[PDB]
């Protein structure tokens, strides 16, 4: 009942398309965690920044692994096969400074 108007959606490459955001959570060896909202398709590097920016801890000293998956600032939520309320594990180990 929000809007009963007919959307055109005539032409689009996938940018004018409707997209929803999902929220996830990641925990590190620091016993800390962060909750973020990302898109179905996007780069997880944004959450890395937000982690270092919010917790003030160096995202380089540790890495982001999803149940054994390696996420090096390029992997996407769509590629990992995951969804909202998902958990990522941050292990402490140099990932190449």
Image (tube, helix red, strand yellow):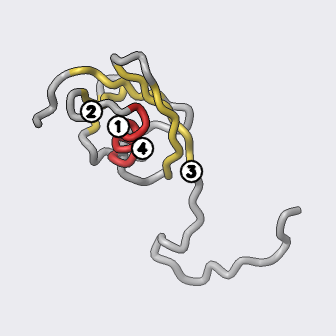
Asked if residue 72 is positioned above or below residue 20 in the image, the reply reads above
Q: CA distance from mark 1 to mark 2?
A: 6 Å
Sequence order check: which comes first, mark 3 or mark 4? 3
Asked if residue 22 is positioned above or below residue 12 in the image, the reply reads above
In the image, 85 versus 8, the foreground residue is 85
Looking at the image, residue 1 sits to the left or right of residue 43; the answer is right
Sequence order check: which comes first, mark 4 or mark 2? 2
Q: CA distance from mark 4 to mark 2?
A: 22 Å
Q: Which residue is mark 3?
A: 21
User: Which quarter of the rendered picture does the C terminus lie within?
Assistant: top left
When asked about the image quadrant of residue 50, the answer is: top left
Residue found at x 42% / y 23%: 27
Confirm or deny contact between disc 1 and disc 4 (CB under 8 A): no
Q: Which residue is mark 4?
A: 77
Residue found at x 24% / y 27%: 62
Sequence order check: which comes first, mark 1 or mark 3? 3
Question: Residue 42: percent from the left, percent from the top?
Answer: 40, 53
Looking at the image, residue 94 sits to the left or right of residue 30; the answer is left
Question: Residue 41: percent from the left, percent from the top?
Answer: 44, 53
Q: Which residue is mark 2?
A: 58
Q: Which residue is mark 1?
A: 52
Count of marks overlaid on the render: 4
Residue 37 tag number:
none
Residue found at x 24% / y 40%: 72
Closest to the camera, between mark 4 and mark 2, is 2
User: Which quarter of the rendered picture does the N terminus lie within?
Assistant: bottom right
Sequence order check: which comes first, mark 1 or mark 2? 1
In the image, 96 versus 83, the foreground residue is 96
Circle 2 residues within 10 Å: few <14, some 14–19, many ≥20:
few
Q: CA distance from mark 3 to mark 2?
A: 26 Å
């Amino acid at each position: 009942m929000s809007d009963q108007e007919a959307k055109p959606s005539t032409e689009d490459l996938g940018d004018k398309k409707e997209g929803e955001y999902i929220k996830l959570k990641v925990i590190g060896q620091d016993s800390s965690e962060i909750h973020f909202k990302v898109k179905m398709t996007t780069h997880l590097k944004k959450l890395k920044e937000s982690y270092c920016q919010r917790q003030g801890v160096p995202m380089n000293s540790l890495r982001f692994l999803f149940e054994g998956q390696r996420i090096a600032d390029n992997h996407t939520p769509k590629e990992l096969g995951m969804e909202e309320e998902d958990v990522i594990e941050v292990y402490q180990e140099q990932t190449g400074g």
